[PDB]
Length: 223
Length: 224
Image 1 (tube, rainbow over the protein chains, first blue to last red):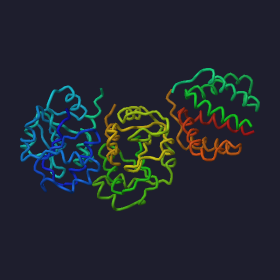
Image 2 (image 1 turned 90 degrees about the vertical axis):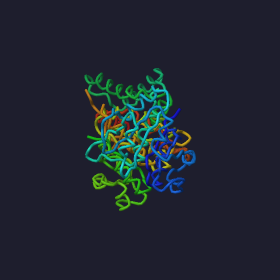
Image 3 (image 1 turned 180 degrees about the vertical axis):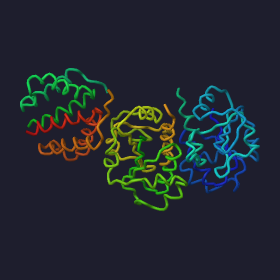
Image 4 (image 1 turned 60 degrees about the vertical axis):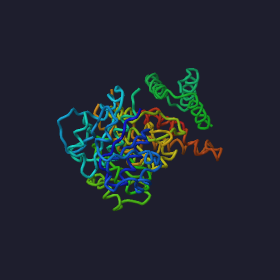
């Protein structure tokens, strides 16, 4: 149904709440915790999660990384982390494509923001997730790591003009208002002047309501 | 060049630095702040940016959204919900594609966290960016919206461009000054949406400097 968002060794309770808020922003409620450094349940995660309180109470905690992964058929490690590699890598745009092709049992790992995924924890994954970032800075908050893969997953990738008789009357009313004030000179330039003024007004391809707004603007300006 | 990230009336300085950290993560460095609620500069934005100090050092503050965007031929309004004004809408992936093709200066607006942009601020933009958040929990963190738009923009993928907003604002003000004399703004309760419908249909055409220049000469001729 929805990928598990497995957080590996969370350290701040505040960081757990931000990622849960990022998950519910794009429709994910499957939060899984693996040995949070302060332990679970935590109350510090509450306010940081904003209205995603349900994702926290529905969280499933596991003693080990392997127990969190036991349900899933496929494992993704988001090592946006100083490792490694020896396993195939794909961008969050590429990972979300295959997961929608896959059936079924996806689980995605995120390491701690301070230290990142540990050697044994990365080994469980069949694929590495990495966020393209410029090396000049190249480091994210863990909630920023979760929101991006959650956003690519949610993407799925699964008026009018004019009518002509009013667009004609509007261009003709403006032209007669300009023609009364001597706008169309010199005579050789007149066809060129009307072309730019027409191209000025046919370019927008504005709606019927916008044409009435134009006619009421000219009606007062002509008065 | 690169698109400008324009923060309209941010409330937390912690969000102001968190977004500049999101900007530098994905190649952005042009922060602009429209009257920050706690003011500028503040230390509290400092640590939240972590190492993205360069953006806050280069950040510049403007009294008005139009002054923050005066150099931008194209203006985008980021939203998390259906907005009342009628503007073209595109996903951040779609907006990032046109922003790559577009020239003359792009500036994206971002509203205060939870509250979002004012309706007047959305009208100033030519195009809307709806982040496809869940409608029942459509409340992104301000920096979280900045990182999604910057993330899609980072994914790399004649020609006369639109006039800068300072030219479009001048032609709009030249028209409103002309219209104020003739009583055009007169159902008084309706005035704020009268200016809003007028600003939208003049920002819709996306016509260039010479076309705005031709429009100004048509107006001065109508004045006479």
